[PDB]
Amino acid sequence: AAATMGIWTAQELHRIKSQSYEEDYPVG
Amino acid sequence: AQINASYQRDMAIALPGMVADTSKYNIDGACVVNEGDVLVGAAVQVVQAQAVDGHKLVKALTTGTTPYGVAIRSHWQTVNAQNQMIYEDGGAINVMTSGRVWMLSKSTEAPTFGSAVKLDVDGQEKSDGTIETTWTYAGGWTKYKDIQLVEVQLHQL
Amino acid sequence: KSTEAPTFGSAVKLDVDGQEKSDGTIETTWTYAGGWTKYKDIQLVEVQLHQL
Amino acid sequence: AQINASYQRDMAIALPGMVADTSKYNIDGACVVNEGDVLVGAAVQVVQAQAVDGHKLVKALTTGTTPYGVAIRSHWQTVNAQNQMIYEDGGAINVMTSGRVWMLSKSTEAPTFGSAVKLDVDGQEKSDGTIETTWTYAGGWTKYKDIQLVEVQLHQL
Amino acid sequence: SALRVFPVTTELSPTDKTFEYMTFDKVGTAQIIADYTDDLPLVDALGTSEFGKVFRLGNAYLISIDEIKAGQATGRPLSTRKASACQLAHDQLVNRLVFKGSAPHK
Amino acid sequence: VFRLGNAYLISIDEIKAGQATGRPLSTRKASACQLAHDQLVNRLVFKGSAPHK
C-alpha cells in the first residue's frame, strides 16, 4: 500500500482558458 | 566523552512494472484501453486488433484468456490514481512484448531460473496460477516496502 | 488468396506457391498480426515472422 | 430589405436552498456535520448537543427522526460535489431554524397555503411523506430547469 | 477542408494535457410592495465548468544507400516522395479525427 | 401610480474572497436586481396584473 506514484501532479499540466461565457437575458 | 557514529542505508532494487536490463526489448504503442483501468505491473489481453486503422484494443486480463504483454512505467502517460500509477480508459499504453520487466507477485516462495510463468485471473504472477504463459523467470526476486516483485522474461506472441 | 479476415493470434498456413491461404497445406510457425486490407484488386495480409 | 427582431427572456425565480425573503429569520452556526454529506435543499437531524462546548452534531434525515432545520446556500462554506452544492464531513454548516426557504421537492401537485409540510426519509419535501413536520407551506411553487422547488415557512423547535 | 471551415486557435502550449472553460448564471425576481413592507425578494448566482484532452501522432519511413545514390544520379529522389507521403498521412489522419472520430479513443 | 422593490444579502467572507480573486458577487447581485426590476416593468406593460387591476 506504499506510494509508488509519479513526480508530476495533475495541475502542473493544465490550462484554464481566458474566455468565460455569460448567458444574456434581454429586457424587452 | 562521546563516540562519533555513522550510519548507512541502501536503496531499493526496483519498483513495480519497470524494465530490468538493457537487453533486447520491444515496446508497443498504438494501444488503447477499451474499458477499465490497467495497473502498471499487470498482464494485458487483446480484445480486438483493427484491420484498417491498426490500433489494438487492450484490456485487463480475465479468466480463460491468453496474456499478450505487460505495461511499463512512465512519468508522462500514466495517470496518478489509487495512490499509484495507472492507465485510464481511452488512453494509450506502453505494453512490453519482449524483454525483462519487474512484475507484481502474489507468491511467497522464491522461484527457479528457467521455469514457465503462471498468472492468476487478474494478471499478477502466482505460483499455482490457472493461466499458463510461454514466458520464463529471470532470477530477480525482491520486494519494495510491503509490495512483492518478481522479474520475468517475456517473448513475442 | 483467402477471402475472410483472420484472427489475431493463429498459425499462418501457406499454399504450394508461398501465398497465404486459410485452408493451405504447408504449416508455418508464424502468426498473424491483424492487418487485413486490399490494394486495388490485390488482397494483402500482415503476418509476424520468427527466426528459424 | 429585412425586418429587425427583438427577443425577451425572463430569469428563474429562485435556486434550491436559498433564503426566500427578508422576513424574520434565524440562522444557527456552530454545527458540524457528524457523518456523511448534506445537500443544500434538505433537512437535517440533531445527533447530539454538547453540554459544555456548545456544538451540535448534525446529520441528514433518516427514518423516524424529527427535522430541525434546512441548509442554506453559501458561496464560501460549501464545497462543489456531483455538479451540485454540498456540505462535506467536518467543517461548519448553516442551518436555519426559523424563516422561509426554497426546498427540494418530489411532489407533482401544487400545495395549499396553510397546510403542514411532510418530508420523506431522505429529508426532501413530499406530498405523502411519512415524516410529519410542524412547518407550513408558503405558496411558492416553481421549477428551475429540471429541479422542482417549493417554498416552506419554518418555525423554531 | 477540416481546418478551412472551422476556426483554429493557439492557446495551448505543447506541454499541457488538459484544458478548462467556465460559465455563469443568475436568478432573481421583483414584486410590488407597499409602505412598511418588511418582506422583499432575493437573488443569487451560480457557475460550472468543463474539460478536454490532447493527443499525439507519429509515423516513419526507411531508405538505403544505393537508393540514395541512384536517386542523386537520375534526378528523381525517393526521400522527398516518402516524406511527402508521411506528411500527407498526418494531414488525412487529422481530417479523419475531425470529421469521423474514433470510438475506442472516445 | 405604483411602486416596486427587492433586496439581496452578502457576508464579510464572500466580500474578502471576491476582493482576493477578482470575481465580485455584489456587482452580479445588483445587476440581477436591476434586471428583475426592468423585466417586471416590461411584464406590467405588456401583460398586466389581474388582482392589482
Image: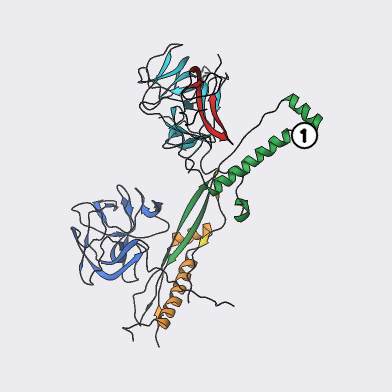
Chain colours: A yellow, B cyan, C red, D blue, E green, F orange
Q: Position of residue D152 (x, y in %)?
A: 27, 66
Q: Nearer the viewer, residue E11 or D59?
A: E11
- Above or below residue E29? Residue B71 is above
- Above or below residue C19? Residue A18 is below
Q: Secondary structure at mark 1?
A: loop
Q: Position of residue E26 (x, y in %)?
A: 44, 65
Apparent side of residue C48 relative to residue E66 in the rendered image (left or right): left
- Under mark 1, the amino acid is Arg
Rendering quarter of residue D22: bottom left
Residue at (48%, 66%) from the top-left corner? F28
Q: Nearer the viewer, residue D112 or D2?
A: D2
Give the number of marks: 1
Which chain is mark 1 on? E
- Above or below residue A3? Residue E20 is below
Apparent side of residue D30 relative to residue B13 in the rendered image (left or right): left
Q: Which residue is mark 1?
A: E76
Residue F23 in view in this figure: no
Q: Nearer the viewer, residue C52 or B152?
A: C52
Q: Nearer the viewer, residue F10 or D139?
A: D139
Q: Position of residue D77 (x, y in %)?
A: 40, 55
Residue at (32%, 71%) from the top-left corner? D23
Rendering quarter of residue D146: bottom left
Q: Position of residue F13 (x, y in %)?
A: 44, 59
Instruction: Spot the residue most to the bottom.
Output: F1
Apparent side of residue D123 relative to residue B133 in the rendered image (left or right): left
Residue E63 in view in this figure: yes
